[PDB]
Image (spheres, helix red, strand yellow):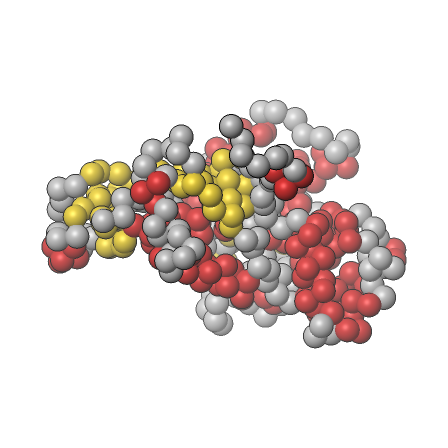
Length: 346
């Protein structure tokens, strides 16, 4: 029967991030035995904490025999956000598009980006490389997949608890800033929401001094988190601009129509809603614009009117997450702009 008696320590609280693993994958993820995957995960977490501005939650790993021996699952708050296979004794050969040829093993697709690839035996490692393929080991596949997911759900992985944690970290470097800012001027809720909207659109939040000072300035006369988000953005323009347009190069961007922005801008006032027809119009055209830029080699950046950006981003992104939506009040003052793509009368 159930040897010991049941207690409250038998209640398992859900995890922010977690991974379920087949039994063949227990070795790499093993605690005792330096878990090959464990260290990769530590690396991934640190890199996120230094590039994005916040430590992702610990990844809770537990085996689950109902799963295929080599399968693994990645969960967020208990729900599956990803899953794949990884065969220990093997290596994965992924084609970047460049390399050519075919190899033995099992045919599949890189979990992250989604490139064709093949699973091969330890032996053929060399050939796979001479033939061009990028060769990584089983544990690495998983780390790559996990890293892709943390990036993708970076906004959701950032909760009230992480907000507080960041706030504490900032306090221990700039005591002044924080101290009397929250719950005083800004509430944790508003802080958390603003920071989330920033991560939501890939804007790093490492520059807390700028963000906190900007809120300290406007919070008093503006409490809407959506509003504050817009302000903090321009306040961060030098970073945002430099992010997608490194160096003193020329800023090649996508632009919408002049009559179109009137269409949108007008309906913006009348009710916080939107009407069909137009919906699919944009989504369609836009998709085409990305490709023009794609072919050209320029960033998937769409520069548009300030009052627009908010709903134009939250609209075209819940479809084309790959698209960046900057405001004209965000792009740096002294940059050479060239609207090298549009959304006109075709």
